[PDB]
Structure formats: structure tokens, C-alpha cells
Image (tube, coloured by chain):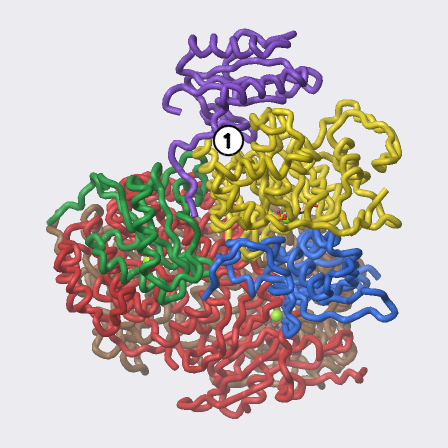
Chain colours: A purple, B green, C red, D brown, E yellow, F blue
Amino acid sequence: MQVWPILNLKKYETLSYLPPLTTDQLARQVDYLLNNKWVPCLEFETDHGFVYREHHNSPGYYDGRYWTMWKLPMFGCTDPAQVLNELEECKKEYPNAFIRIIGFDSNREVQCISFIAYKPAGY
Amino acid sequence: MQVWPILNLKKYETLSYLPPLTTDQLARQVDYLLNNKWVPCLEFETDHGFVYREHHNSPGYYDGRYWTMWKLPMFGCTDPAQVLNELEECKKEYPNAFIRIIGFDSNREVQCISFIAYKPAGY
Amino acid sequence: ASVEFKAGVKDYKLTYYTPEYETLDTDILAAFRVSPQPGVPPEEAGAAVAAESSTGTWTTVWTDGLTNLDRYKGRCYHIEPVAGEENQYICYVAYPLDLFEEGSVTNMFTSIVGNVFGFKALRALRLEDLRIPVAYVKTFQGPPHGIQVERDKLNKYGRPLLGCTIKPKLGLSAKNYGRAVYECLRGGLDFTKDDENVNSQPFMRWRDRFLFCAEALYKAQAETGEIKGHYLNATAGTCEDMMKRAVFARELGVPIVMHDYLTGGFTANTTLSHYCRDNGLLLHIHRAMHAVIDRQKNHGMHFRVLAKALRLSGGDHIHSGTVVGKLEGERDITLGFVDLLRDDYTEKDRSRGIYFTQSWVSTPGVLPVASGGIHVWHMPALTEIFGDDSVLQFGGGTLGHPWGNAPGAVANRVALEACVQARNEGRDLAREGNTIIREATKWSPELAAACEVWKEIKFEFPAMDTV
Amino acid sequence: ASVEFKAGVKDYKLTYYTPEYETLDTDILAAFRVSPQPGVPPEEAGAAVAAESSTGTWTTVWTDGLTNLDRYKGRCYHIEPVAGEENQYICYVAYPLDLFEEGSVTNMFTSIVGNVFGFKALRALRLEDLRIPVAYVKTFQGPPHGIQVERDKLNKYGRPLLGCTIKPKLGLSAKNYGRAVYECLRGGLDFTKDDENVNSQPFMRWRDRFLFCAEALYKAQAETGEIKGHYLNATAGTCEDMMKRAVFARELGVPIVMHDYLTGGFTANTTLSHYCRDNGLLLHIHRAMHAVIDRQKNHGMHFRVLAKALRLSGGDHIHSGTVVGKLEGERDITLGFVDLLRDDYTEKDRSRGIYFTQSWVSTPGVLPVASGGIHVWHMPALTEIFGDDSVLQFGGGTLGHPWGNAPGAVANRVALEACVQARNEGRDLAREGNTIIREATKWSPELAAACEVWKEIKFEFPAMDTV
Amino acid sequence: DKLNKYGRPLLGCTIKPKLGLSAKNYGRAVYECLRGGLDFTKDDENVNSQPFMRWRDRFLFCAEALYKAQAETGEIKGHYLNATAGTCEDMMKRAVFARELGVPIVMHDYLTGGFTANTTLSHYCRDNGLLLHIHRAMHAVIDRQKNHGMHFRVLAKALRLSGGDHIHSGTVVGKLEGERDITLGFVDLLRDDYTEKDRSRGIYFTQSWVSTPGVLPVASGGIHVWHMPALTEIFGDDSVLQFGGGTLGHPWGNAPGAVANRVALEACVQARNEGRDLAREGNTIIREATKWSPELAAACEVWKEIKFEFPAMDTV
Amino acid sequence: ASVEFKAGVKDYKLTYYTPEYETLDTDILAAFRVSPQPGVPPEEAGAAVAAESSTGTWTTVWTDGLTNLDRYKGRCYHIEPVAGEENQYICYVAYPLDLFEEGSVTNMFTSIVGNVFGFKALRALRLEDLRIPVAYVKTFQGPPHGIQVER
Ligand SMILES: O=C(O)[C@@](O)(COP(=O)(O)O)[C@H](O)[C@H](O)COP(=O)(O)O
Ligand SMILES: O=C(O)[C@@](O)(COP(=O)(O)O)[C@H](O)[C@H](O)COP(=O)(O)O
Ligand SMILES: O=C(O)[C@@](O)(COP(=O)(O)O)[C@H](O)[C@H](O)COP(=O)(O)O
Ligand SMILES: [Mg+2]
Ligand SMILES: [Mg+2]
Ligand SMILES: [Mg+2]
């Protein structure tokens, strides 16, 4: 009987309870996003990797949900390499930030994909 | 006339004002809870050993009262050695955690025993 | 069945003495200790009590015919002479469920105890016990929280809680009150409290006291790492004032307030109890004035009845006596109403003055509070009599310590924990009590100082209220 | 002056027995009938009472030094042995004005009667009287209207008012209640009333009763051309419920409501009294439960103290006993507290149990209500004892009439007016009482019928509460 | 958008036993469940305010518990606090305290409480930013038999109008009845903006919603780790899968129970995203995950042979 | 006293079928017309109904050990066949007073009729009657007036 660890066990939503994604596994997630004709976008954050509540405590209000946009959503992107290239570009420029890849469905106007693609040292 | 100290005088509820419990004394407390047919359970905490108020300040609300359960309550336990063994196991896995032993009374549904069995260095 | 109206006076026993009646599980049963005037037979005395506390008056009224009196009348169904007393009887009276207003302790006492105690035909009258049927019990909210929930909110388990009344009773300023409070709390006590008569006065207005006391308790809590409380007294002259005090306490985020239920009254106590339930505030009840009613054996109301009434109206704590302190309280009788306050079921037991079996249908239990003239040497006895589910309070016993409030609290906390440890290890508190305390004095200077001051202090007098 | 703190217990008399003290006109003075345990000297017993009802506790506390105890302490300043009793003393205690919360009868009793009655060192304790200083009296609203204003609102002068409690006590339906009420009112009575225990129950909910009773009283008023009232009972389990009942009565436009002040409590009574003042409603006060507290001479609180407290808290009427009825009440003692309820000034008079001179600084007077076991033959005595400023109530004495409610009321109204006329003409009611009644029976068939039924009915028993 | 959760079904859990737990024991169970990976926990439908646990006490301890779990994991958590009461006034009193606590979600039994009370609460939740979870207790009294009553699809449409953010939809594979095609029919009626007539799925009329928000279907009732592939395949990402016994029945406790469910779900999501057929490769995907997840391995072992197969009463 | 926890599914009848139980005057009693699926024993179907309308679920949970399940559980205490009827029974279930919210019909029905009617193991289910104990009746206001007052 194992006791689930309490320390340094922060998670990052979808796919975070699985083993780290290998190069090919990550590329397959991107392929999935593109195959569904969703728009890819990269977001990064250096100061608040996790949700907190500083400005308000009313129902549904949380700080830390918004991250900062890397360039612009990749409208018309049909090649995973492009997304993976931008990811590297973002890493070299923000090696100490958390970086996630999201995919927008413009018809429903809902993010259908969202997973952490990179974590700074210490995580 | 002695002045009661102010610094580094945090307490841990029942038994915390007596000299540190010896191995034999600790075992006697465990015998007691078992003799009363209460269910033993171990709890540990690393980040917040004492109550505080971060999320709310209304009457009766306090953060830090819940610690995390080590495995499950020992239903059917009748051997004190079983409890002390778990204490040692919890201690080795979490050396920097405060660990307490509690005893449940299922009929009244209240903890009839609760005491700190171990505290990290500097406490 | 109908009958012709005949004006005139008849004996109460013709309609109200029903020795063949079998009580319904929905009836409120009462045990009265009746002392009739010479010449008044016990059957007539018992019937008068039943009649005038339910449906009858002194002469025949025609209006009885518009209703079904058999269905509503109170009935004296049993009488027994009291041993060791002359011309005294225990009369049992049954009242149907319909006579009472749901959830009103005020209405219940108005009928049962309203006018009958002043009857010319009686020398004295005492209400010893009431059997409250479960159907009526369910109409009350009961304690706003109760034993389990309280321990859970405060995160305190495995030992009696510790309190202390600030002294002097009256005369201290708001700031000095907070000063005394912080010093008491930092030394190990769980609570401190306003004296029962400390409401709002020229020397200390309530709001100032609430404010300074909140600062003091939060400082002591931060210093010790143990949850603290201070019973803020909401007792006031009007419902409106009482409410304004409870409201501010809520605003401060403190865990507990107090109320003098008898001097304040049942109507106001029930209002406060509901507010405490709605707002998460623990409610400590002080029984000021009870002895005016419950001390004499021949006339009045026994405390056990006043205790049951509080459990119904609502209160998380209630003073229960100390047995060994400065105020009267016999051990057997005390243990009797303590079970009636904490348990879900108590069987009829006349050796402890319990006249009827009482069930509570899961109404939360009330925490008995032992306070008044107690000190360190009394710790083993108090721990042995009340057990873990109790609050032991030391006012003079803390502020009377030669080294001050913090050392006084330490002495009390250490004395308690030493008893808890010894008991847990299998030692006999009633036999080894003094030895256990002496052992702790060896390593606790604070406790040693307390022990020497109160060594020869005892309170032993013949009790008036006995069985 | 400063002094070194010395821990330990001292006798209460070293600080609380002050036989050389001269009382200030701002002090609350109390007269306690103290019965000490054997071995406890009267000076120590009196001092314990003074101490624990003001500022002290069982052991020395250092905090006394933060304040000026001489300025706040209660003081036993006089002791006298009681004649005809053994080991009993009257101890006089003075409490400074500062100890009390303005306008709160609840706070006043909490201090004076709070914990002292249960002291192990005492066998029994009774509070006989309180001298309420005029400076404290002014902090209370007093009766919402009082004698003069009431007579003026109702347009009734020159004779005692007449009431009647509807019977049976419990069991009648709302419509039958109104039926009984209209019949009683149309025959000449000024008021009818809910029985003290009639609040809201399965057989008759309050709102239905209020509604049917309003219809009945308006019909009787229209028929007779005399202003009528029916005491609608606002006694309830919570302040909120009590208030909802008072509010509906206000909406109906009726003139008077009632409250059981002791079972309801002082906090709720004071709230209702203020509402009655703000809304023009007369307030009748029923003293249910008083005898539990005030019947025995050796322990409790005399009724005169409970009466003064009502005048302060507020009430337009208050039951005062009948002397000749079914409930206890001695003539001299009764007349004593009747003056304390109506007058602006009453001088100390020990033959009537008045221990202190009392001034009311124009606080309105309260109308004493004589009720309980009285009938037509008692009319001359009642009229002679209470005078015009009183309310005489006949429940069983009206609804027990062989011809019904209206004829019963007529018999009572005629019997009263015959006494009023005879008195006014110079006849002696105490001497010619029976003759006066007999003369009226000659032309009043209704009164003749009443007289024959209750001819041999008397209530004569030895009183427990005497002087 | 409020919870910051995308790309997978949400995971919930009903605390057990249904009744009988104290307020503190409720919060204790809640904290352990949420910390293991579940997004939500919930009061059982019949947990309102009773002698063993009064409502305000429960709301208080559950709030302390969920905030602790959230801080530990870094993921937004919630606990459906039950606002169902005997009167509108009591219901509102419970919704108000939830709002004061700053929590994200409350729940209501719309059929036993009633449509009038539900619409009142729906409007209050909109004005105060509270998510509203709807339990369909009593629906089977009305919708089970094919010959008499009202089909659930009509009750589902009624809820979308009255108002609710979630509504139980059945599991198909669980302990309670629900046919696949009929279920798929009303799930579309709950989430989409337009659904055309389709008699094979019991859809008699074409229905348009003119942009009325979709409601999240909640699959709950007798389900476990082995059902994960099937549930993910049937419902898709826009659903909430709840495991009461399936979490509190785990041999290692609540946190490991939650981990098992969260891992099983993510394994199915990853496989699906890679193009794997959940219907055919379901068991394989789960077995693969047990190689690196002790929590999941222990769970699979316990419920390997448990299935719920009986003839359906409600059919097309 | 308590036993060890063992994960796994057990038949509901093991805990919820109590044919020798004597009802208390504070219990809410329910009479159900139960029509089990073929192969489901009436004791199990009756136990399932009692279990899922009170304290139990489909698999064993360790939390039961924190309470005294015996005083809170619903209990199928009696079963009788329906005359001239194929595989149909009247199952009697007792519910302790503590399971219900005072004055709330909504809560009473949520428990007794909440989820059991949709069980796969049952073909049909009908609640015929309920014995409402007087202690529970007193927690309600009832008619605002009633026959007598209305007339
Ligand atoms: O005023 C007092 O005497 C106390 O503060 C005790 O002070 P000490 O701790 O300083 O003695 C308590 O209120 C009494 O115990 C009440 O009596 P009971 O508890 O019997 O109702
Ligand atoms: O319940 C009763 O007995 C009465 O209605 C009298 O009825 P009858 O007129 O039918 O006797 C009165 O309340 C008592 O007088 C109260 O006692 P006191 O007035 O002494 O407080
Ligand atoms: O009470 C219950 O049985 C549940 O908590 C599930 O518990 P388990 O997770 O322990 O099965 C749910 O409320 C049901 O799913 C209701 O049915 P439906 O979703 O079909 O409305
Ligand atoms: Mg006190
Ligand atoms: Mg009366
Ligand atoms: Mg459920």
C-alpha cells in the first residue's frame, strides 16, 4: 500500500499524470490538434505557474489562469514542424518559463487542446 | 518568579505540556486507545504544522486543521506493535513532517485520542 | 357522549385523578414532589396540580362540553409517599402532546409550572423531572453544534477543555480585560470568558471589550499554535441589543459567545441559539439565577429539568457544578444530569434522581462546564468525575497564581495533562490523585508554586439538595 | 494607595463587611434574608454574598490592583437577627451605580441574584427588597402607558375594570374561543383574555384565534357602546415569533396584548414593552412561574422585587393576587407591593415588608390585576382592598354561571357597580358587604343566580409567605 | 474557461456511505479524493441537512478540504455543495453561504426540489457566478417504462431551459439503465445547438436551441477503471465521469483511488489522440498503463470481473 | 469494535436483508412492489433497494468504518409474494429517523425514490405506501388551516 506523495507534486492538467512525453508522443499530440483543424497557439508564464487568488475571492474568480501569448495563434498552419519549431524558439528565449500548447476551435470558441510542453528547471 | 517564554514555544495540543514521551510512555498511550476499541490512524503534515487563516475568517473556519492520512485507519488492529511499526515507516518516508496518532470512536464518530508522535528538526 | 351542564364546584379528583391511566409515548410526563396543606388528601392535591396546569379551573364551566376534555386534560396517574419526609408525595402527571407549542420551552414551562406552585391548598411544590417524548424533542433545534462538532471545529481531542473567568468580576477596563485574556490564553488554557454580569457598563462598554479581547486572543493563538476562544457575553436588556452583540462577534470571526439563559430568558435564548446555528458560532450558556429556583428540596424546580430545557432551547456548553468547589452539587445527582446533557439515552435511575427514561433522538449533546472555587489539587477528582467531555474553568485559580496569569494557566494545563497521562496509563485518579500532582510538581515550577498556595483549601458543607 | 499582591485566600469580611458605610443615593440597596451553615458567622455570610455578587471571588487575584476596588465593591453594611427564626439574619448590601447596565433588568438580576444562592456556606437565601435609586430608574422606559393613559384611551373611570380568562385553559378551537369572548364581553365585562398557556397549539393556532377574537370583540363593542378589549397572548418561543404576533394585533387595531414575562424572560419582555410604546398597544403582564421563586419565606425572591422589575422593564397591568382567592396572598404584604406598583413614592414600612423607601420619579404606575378563584361574594372585599385602580378578573366566575357567559358577566358588572355605589354613598364595604350584594339580588336575576351557586365557596388556608 | 480545464472529460466522485458521515469526516474524505487527481467530489443527492451532519458545518469543512487539495496539486478543484432544501428560503440560504465561501459549484435535485425552485436557483447562480450541477433523482419513477410516463429526453430538454450546467445522463455500462443509442440521442439534445429528427435514436422532432448554452452530461453510477475506454468513447471530452465506489472502494484509499481513475482516463485520452481505437484496444490500453501505475494495477485487480448486463426496459 | 476493510463487491443481502429486524416507532417504513429481473433473488433485489436508498453503493468502501452503519442503514425486514403474479413481491424497508431532514418532503423522497427505480437488476418498482412516524410528522407544519378552520 503506497501513500500518495505530498511534496513537489504539482500537476499541469491534461496528460500530466502520465509519464513525460517522448519526442514522438509530443508530435502525435500536435498531429491530433491539426487533424481536427484546430488552431495551434503557444503560451508561456514565468512568474505564476499556478492559480492563486490575490485580487478577489468570489465564485469562479482566480488569478493565474491567463498566461502570455507567444506571437499569435497559427492560423492556416497545417504542418506540425512549424508548431514544434516555435516551441523551441520559445524555449531558447524563455528557458525559465512554463510553456503550454493550446488548440482553438473557432466554431465553438473553446480550447479543445491544452497541455504543458515544457517546464523550467526545478519542475 | 519565572516569566513564561514567548519564542519557540509552539504547542501540539494534548500531552504537549509534559516532558517528551519516552518509547515506553508512547506505547502505553497506544495501549490505551486500543483497550478502548478505538481505531488508530496516523496523519502527517509538512507545509503547515499549525492553524492559520488564508481562505476565510468567519466563525469556526481555520486552515491547517486537515493533515494528510498515512495509508488508512487500522480497522481490526489489536496489536500496538502494528501502530508503532507504521509510525517508524511514516517517519522514514517523511522525516521533515509532523506526525500525529489519532483514535476514532465509530459509534459517536469523534476522535477520542490525538497527539503528536513525531516532529521534524528545529521543533 | 354528552352530559347536562351542572354549575357548581366539584373536587378536582373526580376528573383529574386517573390511577388506571396508561401513559402514551407522546405524553409529557412530570414528577412533582407535593406537600399538601393539612386536611387536603394527596389525591386531591395531585389532581389540583394536574387540572390547573392543563385544562381546568376552580368551578364547573359549560364550555368543557364544546370540546373533548378526556383528550386534553392533564392526569395525575400515580402517587407514592416519600420516605423520610412527612406529608410529602411524588405525584406523576401526564400531559398530552397537543397541549404544547412546538419548539417553545417557554410554552412548556408556562403550562407545567405556571400557576400551580402558588395554590393555597399546597404548602410546597417541586418539579423533579420531565419525560420529554421524542415527538416533541424533534420540534426543537437543540444545541447549535454540540460536543462532536465543537471538538471538530476547534481541533481539540483527548482531554477536558480548560477555561477561566476574568477577575475581578466588575471594574476592569476594556484594555485591561484584553491584557488579562492574552496572558491567560498564552499559558495553555483553551478559553477565557466574560463574567456573567459583564455586559455593558460605565467602566467597560461591550464593543470596546469585544475588540480588545479579539486582539488578545489572536495574539495568544499565534504564539501557541493552538486554537483559542474567549466567551463574549451577548446577554442584554432587549432582543435587539443581544443581537447587535452577537453580530459584532460574528464580524470579528471569533469562535464563541455566551448567554445567561435564565436572566435573559428562554424566548431570547432560543433566538440566539438559532442565530448561532445560522452563523457558525459556538454558544456557552451560563446558568445565573438557577439556585434561586433549584436549591431547596421541598420547593422549586430541580436543575435536571432546567438542564433538559437548555438542551432543547439550545446551548453548546452549560455549567453543571463542580461537586468539590465553592457552590453546591452532590456527586450522584450531578452525574445524573450530566448523562442527561451528553447522552442519547438515559434510563430511569432513582438513586441519581432520574425519574423517567429519556431519549434524545440524536439531538446533539451538551458539554458540561465545571467552574467555581476549584484549583490544581481538585484536578484528579474533576477529571475522574466528568471525563474528557467537559470544560474545567479556573478563574481565581489562574489569576490568583503568585507569578501571574501565564504561569497560572501553565499550572492548570500541566496538572490536567498529568492526570490525563496517568489515567491513560491505567493509574487510579481517585486513589493516586495527590501523588500524580506531586510527581508533576518536580519538573513544573509553575505547578509547584500553585500547589503550595492552595494546599489547605477545601469546600465541605452539608448539601441541601440531596437524595 | 498601592499594596503588594499576596496570593492566597482571605475571609470575605476583611474586604466586604463595611458596617460603617453610609449609603449613597445612587447605590442599589438589597435586603437579603440569610441563613448561614453552622459555623459560618453572619458577618462572613453577608460578606460572601456581597463579594460574589459584585467584584470578588474565592482567592486573592492580582488584577484587583489595576482598578480601584473600593469604588466598585458591593458592601454588606448592616446585619440584624430575625425574630422568630433561628440562625437567620437580614443583611443589607450596597452596590454602586456603575456596576449596572442602563435599562437592563436582566443585568441587574444577573449580579444580585446570579450565583450567590448556591453557595455551600449558606443553607438558604432570599432577596426581600431592592432600593432602586432614581438615577437608575431614569434609564428605563417603564410601562408603555400606565394607569392614567390607559383609563384615558379606553374612556373608563370611577370603578375597577373587569376581566375574565376563557376556559377551559386549553382545548377550545379558534371559533369557539371567539364565541365565548363575544358572549362574555356583551354582558358588561371590559376585557376577556387568553389563558397564559394559550399561545399556538394543534387545537388552536394563534393567527386564527386573533382573527376570530377581533371579530367577537368588535361585535360586542358595537352592541354595548362601551370600549372592549381581549388580551391577545404574544408569548412565544423566540423573539421573532413574539414580534410577529404583536404585529398582527397592531394590524387588527385592537387595544391590548399580553405577555408572560417570567417564562418569556426579561430580555424579550423589554423588547415587547418598547414595541407597545411605539405602537400604542396596552400590555398586560401575566406572572406565570412566580410562585416557583417567591412562595417560601426562607429561600427565593419576594414578589415585590419581581413587581418592581416589571415596572422598570414595562407592563401596563400585572397580576397582584386576590388575597381571598384560590392562590396565596396575604393582605398586608399585598397592599405593600400594590403601592409599590401604583404610587410615585412609598416609605419604608416593615409591617408590610417594605424594607427601603422607594421613589419612582414619575415612572407611570401599573394597574394591579386580581384574578384566580374569585366570585360575586368576594366583590365587596376586592373593591375595598384594591380600590378603583385595579382590574378584577372572573374566569370560572363568569363561564361557570348557570345561564351562560352574558348573564355571568352581567352578574359581575352589577355586583361591582352595587359596591361602587354603596361605597360612594358612604357605606362600609367590609361591614355591609353581604348586605349590599343581597340588596342587588332583589332586582338582578342574573346576580341572584350567581349568588346561590357560589354561596358556600371560600378559600382559607395558612399562608407560607408571611410577616 | 472558468476552471481552466480542456482536452479531456472531467472527473468526479460521490462520497460514501451515502448518509451517516459527520461533517469533519466528510471533509477528510473530500481532501483525500481531490488531491489524487479528481476535479470534483460531491454531496450524495440525499445529503441535505440531517442530525448526523448539518449543512453549514459540512459546507465549512468541505471548503477547507478543497482549498487544501487545490493548493497541493496546483489544479482547480470543486465540491458540489447540495442546496436542495425543504423550502425556497432554505435553499437560498445554502446557496448564499456557498457564495460567501468563494467556492465554484453547488448542486440541486431538480425533480424532488421542483422546477419552480430550480429556476429560482438557476437565476441566482447566473447572478452570482456559481456553477450549477443538477441531479435527476426520481427520474426513473417517471421515465423507466416504455408504455407510460415521460421519456428522459423530455426531462433533459426541460432542464436545459430551466437551467443547469451539468445533468446526469446515465452511463450505459453502469449499475443503472441506459441504452447506448437512446443515450447518445439525448446527449446531443443537451450539448448541441441543433439536432435533426432521428427515430433510430428516439428523436421525434428536429430541435434548434438558438445559442442556448450546452449542458455537460454526467456519467455516474457503478462504473470503474475497466469502463474508462468505453465511457471516453461514448461521451467524448465534454462530459463528467464520476466514480464514487470506484474511488472510495480502492484498496489503498481515496488518493490512490483518484490517481487510478485519473491515470486510466489520461491513458485513454492519449491513446485516442494517437489514433488508437478505444472500442477494440480498450483493455490493452488499460493493461499497458498498469505496468507503470501501481495505483491503477491495484484497482484493475479488484474490479476485473465486474459487469452490469441485464435486459433494458426502455428501448426504441 | 470493527473489522478489517476488504475491497471488492459483496451482495447487498449480506448487509441489508434483515428478516429478524423489529421496526422502531421512529422508523419510516416503506412498502415496495418489486419486480426483479430473471435470476435476481427477491432477497437481493429487496436488499439492493434498501441499500441504495440509504447508505450503500455497488462496492465496499472503507469509510463505512468511520460510522456505525448498523444504526443508519436502510433494512429490508420482510418479503411477501404477490398473489396471481409472476415474480413480483412486496418488500418492506425500514429507514431510521436520523436519515431525514426535518420538515422536508423533498429530502424524504430524494432518499426513498431517488435512484432505485432505475436499477438494471429490477424490471419494475412501485412505492405503495409509507408509514410516517409521529416524531417525523411533528417536524412539519401541515395544512395551513385544515377542515375545521376552513368551515
Ligand atoms: O462568578 C463566578 O463565581 C465564576 O466566574 C467562577 O469564578 P472562579 O473560577 O473564580 O471561582 C463562575 O461563573 C461560577 O462558577 C458559576 O457557578 P456555576 O458554575 O455553579 O453555575
Ligand atoms: O389560570 C388561572 O388560574 C387564571 O386564569 C384564573 O382563572 P379563574 O378566574 O377561572 O380562576 C389566572 O391566570 C390566575 O389568576 C393567575 O394567578 P395570579 O393571578 O395569582 O398570577
Ligand atoms: O447514489 C448513487 O448511486 C450515485 O452517487 C453513484 O454512486 P457510485 O459512484 O458509488 O455508483 C449517483 O447519484 C447515481 O449515479 C445516480 O444515478 P444517475 O447518474 O443515473 O442519475
Ligand atoms: Mg462568573
Ligand atoms: Mg390563566
Ligand atoms: Mg448519489
Q: Please say if E33 is above or below F149.
A: above
Q: Residue at x 55, y 50 (%)?
A: E302
Please state if E173 lies on the left or on the right of A101 as rendered: right
Location of residue C227 in the rendering, given as x and y in whole percent from the top left corner: 35, 46
Q: Please say if C467 is above or below F125.
A: below
Tell me the amino acid under the disc marked 1.
Leu
Q: Pointer 1 indicates a residue of which chain?
A: A
Q: Please say if E201 is above or below E5.
A: below
In the foreground, C38 or C264: C264
Within-10-Å neighbours for mark 1: few <14, some 14–19, many 20+:
some
In the foreground, E88 or F5: F5
Split into 4 quadrants, where in the image is the C terminus of chain C? bottom left
Q: Which residue is mark 1?
A: A18
Location of residue C178 in the rendering, given as x and y in whole percent from the top left corner: 29, 43
User: What is the number of callouts on the image?
Assistant: 1
User: Would you say residue C353 is visible in this rendering?
Assistant: yes
Q: Residue at x 12, y 59 (%)?
A: C442
Location of residue E22 in the rendering, given as x and y in whole percent from the top left corner: 51, 54
Q: Assign ligand 2 to one image quadrant.
A: bottom right
Circle 1: element type: loop
User: Would you say residue E57 is visible in this rendering?
Assistant: no
Q: Residue at x 44, y 57 (%)?
A: B110
In the foreground, C277 or F21: F21
Q: Residue at x 69, y 70 (%)?
A: D166
Please state if B59 lies on the left or on the right of E7 as rendered: left
In the foreground, B120 or F139: B120
Split into 4 quadrants, where in the image is the N terminus of chain C? bottom right
Q: Please say if C203 is above or below C324.
A: above
